[PDB]
Image (tube, coloured by chain):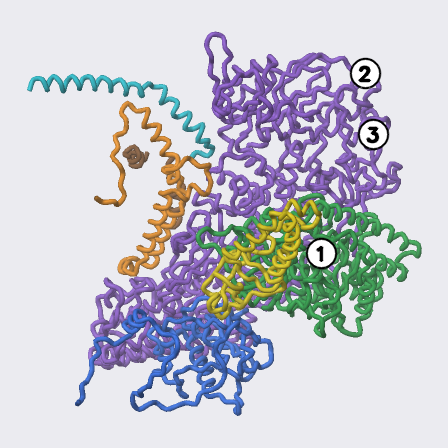
């Protein structure tokens, strides 16, 4: 069973940004005692992290004890760590060395990883057991009891012994903002539906996590629904009952819209190899099942018997009887497949097996060819092939050439051309289309044949199949409809008896009436002996009078079986309108499209050349057909409906039918994300809102797409776990950049139809998008400073602050005397003691002692120089340079302001790790914030960012009673509106700017009943 | 099924072109996926779970109000007959599956920027010839026209057959109990938006009864005590966001059936509607019904904007009309509480507080819309908030009338 | 082209009979052929000239641009459905009746204003 | 909805026979009426359109007919835009045949194959698909200023083209002239220019015309 | 030839050669579908032919782009670092005489 | 970098380059 | 083409080794000597006839 693992409850508090306490506060006992208190001395874990520096790094599910993992997650290690390993999910692997991060393909990665950040959060927030609070900390309240995860959840329940910077903050916490709020329960005594509660959790994870419940809904159906969807699916036969009584809650995501379906049907036809072999386990699948259940017993004896009993003098050499008795004998695999083949004519249309045609060396005096040709006709309508009529006409027209001459269109196609070789629409005998043309006084016999085929080829018709509440996988037929060769009748609930009415039956009766005319005709009558020619009339009349129960079946019970069986089948039926002899509407090609002819300039070019054409044909044998068709018997005492109500019970009792229904939804997602993923990392394609346009991307080459479009196909394959090929095949022609679906057949005449299935309106083409809106806003929380990087030798003694820079940045681009570096970055040397000129932008070598603006890229194919001429300069403190790189990864390094330090080598090294390929995460040294007013050693710094990239600092001295030299950073209240703001209202969150690490949120208790959980079938 | 729908586009509020940005077209109707039955994929169990605050779309209803404007500029087919294109954008094919940049060599005739164009599912001979396929576009133009005929809050419809709930309609609801008003409109919307369902279909009765009960609750009457056939909506206690609603089959006195057919068009009247996830999921839901059933009759003309007069097929004025009432969340809730207070549901001193609780709440979903209004002008070619002038907020519209239309609807 | 502008009332296909004078709440848009703009511009030009005297004496109301009375409609513009069918004009510049009224009474009101001063200057 | 896959579905909007029916022609096409096999679907149209025309021809005020028109109408799987298929061309002509328009060429009371074919031939001949009355799938727009009085239900909209050239009145049938009738020439106002009024003649004149002499 | 444009979906399907490779395959797809073909081409195999020739046409080859944006910049250079400069008589497409 | 892998796949379902380089160097 | 591909860096690295081999100047040199060996050959054979 490979259905996407949809329902995945999570008890532990949903949050994906933990306040990871970084640089710890020094436990100091000798001197300055009391300055910093640790919750630890009161055997009680601190709610907020307690360290000299507490970053808010992001870890999806850090505190997620809830049973069962999602499979993939994204945990950035604190800035103190390296981090770059988390951004090389594409365009890196085996090219950009460990140490670094590919700055060119930055967006392609921060996006491929955010998609990763989303899928990891696609769990349902399951409700836990909210117990009261007998303790005085909350005096009664409804806090949700968990182990130690409690302390970490409700920050409010914190016990504050001393005025510690944390306690400085927590102190505020509005008392009543804890525990739960509105447990909305219905059945008194049954578990609550969805309790509602405030509890540490970021507005973001919350959002995704609940835009998921919104999704599980988009594919749900109350019971009175799922019952009919099931009824209709088996054509009301099959007794299933639903209990009219309130069923608390039941989230059962089994349904996908009709659109979500089609997006996966075409999708499924892309991986299927257009070759006849890939369509064989598509018909044979419907054939083993067709037989599995069917009140149609094939019984040779019947026919054999009816024929063996025609008198035949043995003073004759040719044995009219012995003949067919031989011919009519090559097993029933052919009858079924003919039928089963109807369900998928789009993919594969059956055909009269070339070998089973009277050979083109004999005329109609040959009696083994007279029978061979009779069996071509009868079995004619059975095969789905858009030519059977013409081929049948030829088969005879062909064999009786000498007597009967007829019009034969194109050159190199004589009336004696091996019948079978008449596959093209354009080469139909001019007389065959319009029999008016064939003259009697020349080709009577043949004209009555053309005359016959036209008057009696079965009229196609359509019937319903599946439930209308549950869409359908149709691409060329209305939803819940299947075109069908033979006229159709409603299933009978009484007793059946082989009837002699009906297209099938009539077709056998008139055609067998024609060959009885061929036998009693002038030609025949003069050549073939007499008494033998009677035997042939008898041998045929017998046939045209056997009580075959099949004619009935192909018109009453078969339609029910195809309809009901068009759901149990592991691939929905794929049909194209059946054209009962209409010259122009012969479908030469049923095509599909992996790419869209829009992007590549193919708007005008013909359809047959822009789409792939399924080419799969089965060689059915006329012998089998007839033997079956003309020889079906049933169970004398049989109720058609009853026998089905029985034959369907099993394959309709379980919700296996509902599975493919989801594989469809997950497909409509994987696809809409890929389309988004590739187009974002691409540059302006299928109108996909790019909230990540600022980030970089210099590899838009297909490889880049397939790479992008590939991980996305993993993230999902991993997220929902499904071996089945999903989102694959789209690639094939090696180019995701223009992934676009479209199916469309082409009738010989002209009409091209077209029907390009576009992705349905999906739920993640939101969420992910929603995350990128917010990612942009709060990058830092993922180790990704924005702005640029300055390099100026500032040797201070005060609170150096690389991240959040006070005052205006010195010398912005295009400022007074602030030359850029010309693309190459070359440095021309000058003779007898003169400064080496640094070729500036305008391409006019300027001098290093000044203010430079280094377009990052330049700095990559140039460091060898940078470090040898401008670097020695910056240290001397005479050439402030601005390295201008969009958004970089940023490593921090907290040193100790007490002791002396010179930030030069933790920079020179970073320079020596910049290839024309990739640069290491920009490292910034930062003094660890002290508690007392310590004497500090004059350190020399160089790296310091312009943009305020200090957005995850969270706290400056948790435990310390007050930071003194470091940069005090009291826990920002703006982060905890829910937790400390009086005006905060339960149900509000500035979701696309900040991330409130403490909101309200509905946790559910969804019960997932199975198909027996709903109706009671049997 | 149903093959006939008449729409009316939004009104370019004293503005030039349609108030929707290109950045929007690729924010709802983009990604190439069919922008159709997507309206609902922007709502949560409540409001605290959506990016519906300070942002590109600062409102729990700012999405639909935009997607609706965007639909106006791309519905010329139903207006005249051809497909046309508004600013390098035009449906890819005749089935209007989705939007996409104008081709290159065979571009559709540039649309004609005109406001409030009527629509006829007939002016487009291909629509009905495919019905099944582009079925969605119907129910959508309908969702549009029910927000367009109005200026301050969508105009849905209410019913109550003189008979008891259609059995398989008491069974379908009793499986949607705990479910929030949001996820109800969900199923409601998601339902009548794919495959033409016959108005006779079970679901329509159920989802049409679920729009009659929601209303009874919104006006006390159908409360925890006086339920419909057993149902009524319990609103969250105002103090923690009362902008909620959950279906709850109880077992208290059953509000006896009305003495006749009770029909009426009710629309939220104050700007408040634009941010109350329940005042939208509810209204939006009541519209799910009309979409797959034509349109009961003609919505009364009287109380309605200036661009909605005698709107052929939609608006009326004569007999084929039904008096259209408009309530105000606060003047409403107040009575909704008084009702509870009368049925002993609450204390006599608890309603003079329940209002305080809720009234302060409405004062919050008020300093917010005004803020977003004086944040996203309108001359900025966009309309995520939809102008309203600091006034309608207190506007004690019909209200008193609908509070009575509720009683006669659930006697 | 010349005359009032017409548009296919029956939509899309214009057959010389489908076209009808595109009238409406503003009156009927009559086309403003190249030369007829020369006049109204030459008339307004002679008024703008007196700009320094309009401000001085607080009358007037800013310079009169002829582009304030016209529009940019498009359709077929002729004298009758039959002949208007042979003048498909796109985004031509038409002046609606109610406008042909102001450009008139404005040039008239302003014309008095200046006619007076213009007499003293003389 | 359910029979939308079928080739086409004709339906009588004007007072159906025993109650509203919904004719569905089988896919096959008849042999005889056109060199190009005409689909059974489109043939039914011609046969009926050829009634609304022949019926309009002699319908009078004093008489009361079952249906105010006998023309069929395509409701499904019909291409509304193009004008190729005999059906589309026929349909396009029926939306006009509901106004009371009559064919100049008298349509025989008992249409004969020779005749039907001479009509299905005239229909195929390149021409201009009438455009006064646009086509709908559920409504037949009928000129308000026209003899035809709509039945009742919701199938007839009183659409009025901007300029319909037809006025009302009938025509009394006149028997076939036994010999070529001479026509005195009375002139109009507009005159063609010798140059144009020459080739005009030379584009449709019978130049190398064989002629008998008789006896002078 | 043209100055190497920033890779995208545009320059990589609009190259001179992309057109040629395209319109040709397009043309032959109609040839293998001629009525004449019927004589010896099977209906299934005639489809298999359209199947293959379309694969080629739609295949995402990146040379057409190289031979029209990146290949000139090589020859231009490579044609200077060679001990024997390039002898080259003018090209002519169909101008006959 | 010329390589028929992609081409082969694409085609294979429904079923050194001196020449080339000695064609550009040929121009 | 190779997944990661900055035309700038690629063509750069490739044409580097090429300009290292002074084969561009061998051409100018073998040239000024062929013109010598010609104006001298043509002359010597044009002086004997």
Q: Residue G31 falls in which quadrant of the image?
A: top left
| Quarter of the rendering occupied by the N terminus of chain B | bottom right
The chain letter corresponding to green is: B
Say the numbered circle drawn on residue A167: 3
Residue E54 at x, y = what percent? 38, 50
Q: Which of marks 1 and 3 is in front?
A: 1
Left/right of residue A742 with respect to residue A323 in the rendered view = right
The answer for which chain carries disc 1 is: B
What shade has chain G been given?
A: cyan
Say the numbered circle drawn on residue A695: none
The chain letter corresponding to orange is: E
Q: Residue at 53% x, 45% y: name it.
A: A675
| Quarter of the rendering occupied by the C terminus of chain B | bottom right
Q: In this view, does B260 lie above or below A18?
A: below
> How far apart in space, not on screen, are marks 2 and 3 (Cα)?
22 Å
Q: Residue at 45% x, 43% y: name it.
A: E10
Left/right of residue C45 with respect to residue A582 in the rendered view = right
Query: Label 2 belongs to which residue?
Result: A29
> How far apart in space, not on screen, are marks 2 and 1 (Cα)?
61 Å
Residue B88 at x, y = what percent? 52, 51
The answer for which chain carries disc 3 is: A
Query: Label 1 belongs to which residue?
Result: B281
User: What residue occupies the far left of the structure in this picture?
Assistant: G49
What shade has chain C been given?
A: yellow
What shade has chain A been given?
A: purple
What shade has chain F been given?
A: brown
Q: Residue at 56% x, 13% y: name it.
A: A872
Q: In this view, does A1010 lie above or below A674?
A: below
Mark 3 surroundings within 10 Å by alpha-carbon count, few (fewer than 14), some (14 through 19), many (20 or more): many
> How far apart in space, not on screen, are marks 1 and 3 (Cα)?
42 Å
Residue D164 at x, y = what percent? 50, 75
């Amino acid at each position: 069973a490979n259905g996407p693992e949809l329902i995945i409850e999570d008890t532990g508090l949903c949050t994906s940004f933990m306040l990871l306490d970084n640089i710890p506060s020094a436990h100091l006992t000798k001197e300055l005692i009391g300055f910093t208190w640790f919750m630890q001395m009161y055997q009680m874990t601190p709610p907020l992290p307690e360290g000299a520096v507490n970053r808010i790094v992001c870890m999806t599910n850090w505190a997620s004890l809830g049973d069962e993992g999602r499979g993939l997650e994204v945990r950035l290690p604190p800035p103190t760590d390296s981090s770059v390993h988390a951004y090389k999910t594409v365009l890196s692997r085996g090219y950009i060395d460990n140490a670094q991060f590919n700055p060119l393909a930055l967006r392609s990665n921060v996006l491929l990883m955010l998609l990763q950040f989303t899928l990891s959060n696609l769990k349902i927030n399951k409700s836990s057991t909210f117990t009261s609070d007998v303790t005085t900390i909350t005096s009664g309240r409804m806090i949700r009891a968990f182990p130690e995860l409690l302390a970490l959840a409700y920050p409010g329940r914190a016990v504050l012994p001393t005025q510690t910077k944390n306690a400085q903050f927590l102190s505020t916490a509005i008392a009543d903002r804890i525990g739960r709020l509105d447990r909305a329960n219905l059945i008194g005594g049954e578990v609550s539906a969805m309790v509602e509660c405030m509890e540490l959790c970021d507005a973001l994870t919350l959002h995704i996590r609940e835009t998921y419940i919104m999704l599980l809904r988009s594919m749900h159906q109350d019971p009175t629904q799922i019952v009919q969807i099931v009824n209709e699916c088996a054509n009301n036969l099959l007794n299933s009952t639903i209990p009219i009584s309130l069923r608390p809650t039941i989230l059962c995501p089994w349904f996908a819209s009709s659109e979500d379906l089609r997006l996966q049907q075409v999708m499924h036809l892309v991986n299927i190899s257009s070759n006849t072999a890939a369509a064989l386990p598509l018909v044979e699948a419907l054939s083993t099942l067709l037989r599995s259940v069917t009140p149609l017993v094939l019984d040779p004896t019947v026919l054999t018997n009816a024929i063996t009993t025609i008198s035949e003098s043995t003073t004759q050499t040719i044995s009219p009887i012995s003949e067919i008795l031989r011919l009519l004998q090559p097993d029933y695999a052919a009858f079924w497949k003919c039928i089963a083949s109807w369900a998928y004519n789009g993919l594969v249309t059956t055909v009269l097996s070339e070998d089973a045609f009277p050979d083109s060396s004999q005329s109609i005096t040959h009696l083994p060819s007279m029978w061979k040709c009779l069996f071509l006709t009868l079995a004619g309508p059975m095969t789905s092939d858009p030519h059977s009529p013409v081929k049948v006409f030829m088969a005879l027209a062909n064999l009786l050439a000498q007597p009967e001459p007829i019009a034969i269109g194109v050159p190199g196609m004589h009336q004696t051309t091996p019948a079978s070789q008449f596959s093209h629409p354009g080469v139909w005998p001019p007389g065959f289309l319009n029999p008016q043309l064939i003259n009697p006084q020349q080709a009577p016999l043949l004209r009555a044949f053309a005359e016959h085929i036209r008057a009696n080829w079965p009229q196609p018709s359509e019937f319903g199949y599946g439930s209308t509440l549950q869409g359908s996988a149709n691409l060329f037929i209305p939803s819940n409809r299947m075109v069908y060769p033979w006229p159709n009748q409603p299933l009978p609930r009484l007793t059946v008896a082989p009837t002699y009415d009906s297209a099938m039956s009539n077709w056998i009766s008139t055609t067998i009436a024609f060959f009885i005319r061929v036998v009693n005709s002038v030609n025949m009558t003069a050549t073939v002996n007499d008494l033998t020619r009677r035997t042939m009339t008898g041998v045929m009349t017998a046939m045209r009078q056997v009580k075959t129960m099949t004619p009935f079946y192909i018109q009453h019970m078969c339609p029910t079986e195809l309809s009901v069986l068009a759901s149990v089948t592991v691939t929905p039926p794929f049909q194209v309108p059946f054209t009962r002899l209409v010259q122009n509407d012969v479908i030469t090609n049923v095509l599909v499209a992996r790419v869209d002819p829009a992007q590549r300039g193919d708007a005008a070019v013909d359809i047959r050349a822009t789409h792939a054409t399924f080419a799969a044909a089965l060689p059915v044998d006329p012998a089998a057909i007839v033997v079956a068709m003309l020889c079906g018997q049933t169970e004398t005492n049989l109720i058609p409906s009853h026998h089905y109500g029985k034959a369907f019970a099993p394959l309709f009792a379980s919700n296996a039918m509902f599975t493919r229904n989801q594989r469809a939804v997950i497909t409509r997602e994987a696809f809409v994300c890929a389309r988004s993923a590739v187009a974002q990392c691409q540059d302006a394609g299928f109108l996909v809102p790019r909230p990540l346009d600022a980030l970089r991307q210099f590899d838009v080459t297909s490889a880049a797409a397939a790479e992008i479009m590939h991980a996305v196909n993993d993230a999902f394959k991993t997220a929902f776990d499904l071996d089945g090929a999903l989102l694959d095949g789209l690639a094939l022609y090696g180019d995701p950049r223009i992934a676009d679906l479209s199916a469309a057949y082409l009738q010989y005449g002209g009409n091209v139809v077209r029907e390009h299935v576009p992705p349905g309106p999906s739920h993640i083409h939101r969420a992910l998008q929603q995350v990128e809106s917010t990612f942009m806003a709060e990058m830092n929380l993922f180790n990704v400073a924005r702005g640029n990087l300055y390099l100026v030798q500032t040797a201070t003694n005060g609170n150096w602050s690389p991240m959040a820079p006070v005052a205006a940045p010195p010398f912005v681009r295009g400022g007074p005397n602030v030359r850029v570096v010309g693309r190459f970055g070359t440095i021309v040397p000058r003779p007898n003691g003169l400064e080496p000129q640094l070729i500036d932008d305008g391409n006019v070598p300027r001098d290093i002692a000044g203010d430079w603006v280094y377009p990052s890229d330049v700095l990559q194919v140039s460091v060898a120089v940078f470090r040898d001429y401008v670097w020695p300069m910056v240290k001397a403190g005479r050439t402030r340079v601005l390295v201008e790189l969009g958004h970089y990864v940023y490593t921090l390094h907290y040193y100790d302001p007490q002791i002396s330090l010179d930030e030069a080598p933790i920079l020179e090294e970073w320079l020596s790790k910049i290839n024309p390929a990739g640069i290491p995460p920009v490292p910034f040294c930062i003094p660890i914030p002290q508690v007392y007013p310590c004497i500090t050693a004059r350190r020399v710094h160089y790296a310091f960012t312009s943009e305020n990239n200090n957005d995850s600092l969270f706290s400056t001295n948790a435990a310390s009673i007050d930071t003194a030299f470091g940069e005090n950073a009291a826990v920002s209240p703006l982060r905890w509106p829910g937790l400390v703001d009086p005006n905060y209202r339960v149900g509000t969150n500035d979701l696309p700017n900040r991330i409130t690490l403490y909101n309200s949120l509905y946790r559910y208790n969804f019960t997932y009943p199975t198909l027996d959980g709903i109706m009671y079938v049997r | 099924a149903q093959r006939q729908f008449f729409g009316l586009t939004y009104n370019f509020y004293g503005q030039p072109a349609p108030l929707f940005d290109l950045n929007d077209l690729q924010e709802l109707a983009g990604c190439y996926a069919r922008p159709w039955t997507s309206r609902f994929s922007h709502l949560a169990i409540s409001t605290g779970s959506l990016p519906v605050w300070s942002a590109r779309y600062p409102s729990v209803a700012s999405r639909n109000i935009v997607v609706n404007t965007l639909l106006g500029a791309h519905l010329n087919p139903f207006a005249g007959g051809q497909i046309t294109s508004h600013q390098g954008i035009t449906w890819r094919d005749p089935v209007l599956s989705s939007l996409a940049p104008v081709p290159a060599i065979q571009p559709p005739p540039v649309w004609a920027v005109a406001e409030n164009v009527l629509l006829d599912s007939n002016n487009y001979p291909t629509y009905v010839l495919n019905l099944s396929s582009m079925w969605p576009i119907n129910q959508d133009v309908h969702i549009m026209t029910m927000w367009a005929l109005s200026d301050q809050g969508p105009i849905y419809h209410l019913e109550v057959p003189v008979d008891p709930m259609p059995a398989a309609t008491t069974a379908a609801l009793m499986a949607y109990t705990g479910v929030p008003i949001a996820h109800l409109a969900q199923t409601a919307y998601r339902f009548a938006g794919q495959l033409p369902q016959s108005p006779d279909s079970t679901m329509v009765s159920t989802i049409r009864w679920l729009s009659a009960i929601w209303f009874g609750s919104l006006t006390g009457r159908l409360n925890r005590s006086r339920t419909c056939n057993g149902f009524y909506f319990e609103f969250a206690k105002p103090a923690l966001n009362p902008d909620q609603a959950v279906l709850k089959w109880n077992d208290g006195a059953r509000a006896a059936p009305p003495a006749a057919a009770q029909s009426s068009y009710i629309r939220c009247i104050s700007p408040h509607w634009q941010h109350q996830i329940v005042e939208v999921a509810g209204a939006l839901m009541s519209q799910s019904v009309t979409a797959v059933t034509g349109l009961p009759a003609l919505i009364d003309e009287a109380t309605l904007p200036a661009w909605s007069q005698g709107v052929a097929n939609l608006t009326g004025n004569g007999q084929g009309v039904v008096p259209c009432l408009d309530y105000n969340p606060v003047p409403m809730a107040a009575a909704r509480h008084l009702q509870w207070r009368q049925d002993g549901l609450i204390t006599a001193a608890q309603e003079a507080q329940l209002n305080n609780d809720y009234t302060a709440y409405a004062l919050t979903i008020e300093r917010h819309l005004t803020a977003m209004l004086v944040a996203n002008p309108i001359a900025a070619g966009r309309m995520p908030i939809q102008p309203f002038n600091a006034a309608d907020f207190g506007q004690a519209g019909q209200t008193a009338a609908a509070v009575a239309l509720a009683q006669a609807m659930f006697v | 082209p010349t005359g009032k502008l017409w548009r296919p009332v029956g939509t899309s296909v214009a057959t010389i009979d489908s076209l009808a004078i595109v009238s409406d709440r503003f009156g009927q848009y009559s086309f403003v052929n190249e030369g007829m703009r020369e006049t109204f511009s030459k008339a307004l030009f002679d008024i703008n000239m007196w700009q320094p005297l309009f401000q001085a004496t607080k009358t007037g109301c800013g310079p009169i641009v002829l582009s304030s009375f016209t529009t940019t409609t498009s359709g077929y513009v002729g004298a009758t459905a039959g002949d208007a069918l042979d003048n498909p004009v796109t985004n031509g510049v038409f002046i609606s009746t109610v406008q042909i009224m102001n450009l008139q009474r404005t040039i008239a009101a302003r014309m008095r204003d200046v006619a007076l001063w213009q007499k003293h200057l003389d | 909805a359910n029979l939308a896959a079928g080739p086409t579905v004709l339906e009588h909007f004007d007072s159906p026979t025993y109650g509203p029916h919904l004719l569905l022609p089988q896919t096959g096409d008849v042999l005889g009426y056109s060199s190009s096999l005409i689909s059974q679907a489109a043939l039914l149209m011609v046969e009926s359109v050829m009634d609304a025309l022949r019926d309009n021809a002699n319908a009078s005020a004093s008489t009361a007919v079952t249906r105010l028109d006998q023309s069929y109408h395509p409701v499904t799987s019909f291409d509304p835009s193009t004008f190729n298929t005999l059906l589309q061309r026929a349909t396009n002509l029926a939306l006009l045949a509901v106004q009371g328009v009559q064919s100049e060429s008298a349509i025989p009371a008992i249409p004969t194959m020779s005749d039907v074919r001479s009509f299905v031939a005239r229909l195929m001949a390149e021409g201009d698909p009438q455009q006064w009355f646009p086509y709908r799938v559920d409504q037949i727009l009928y000129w308000p200023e026209s003899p035809f009085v709509p039945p009742i239900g919701p199938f007839y909209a009183p659409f009025r083209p901007v300029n319909f050239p037809f006025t009302t009145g009938s025509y009394t049938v006149v028997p076939d002239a036994s010999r070529p009738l001479r026509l005195l020439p009375q002139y109009r106002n507009a005159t063609i220019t010798v140059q144009q009024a020459d080739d005009a003649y030379e584009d449709t004149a019978l130049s190398p015309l064989i002629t008998t002499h008789g006896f002078c």
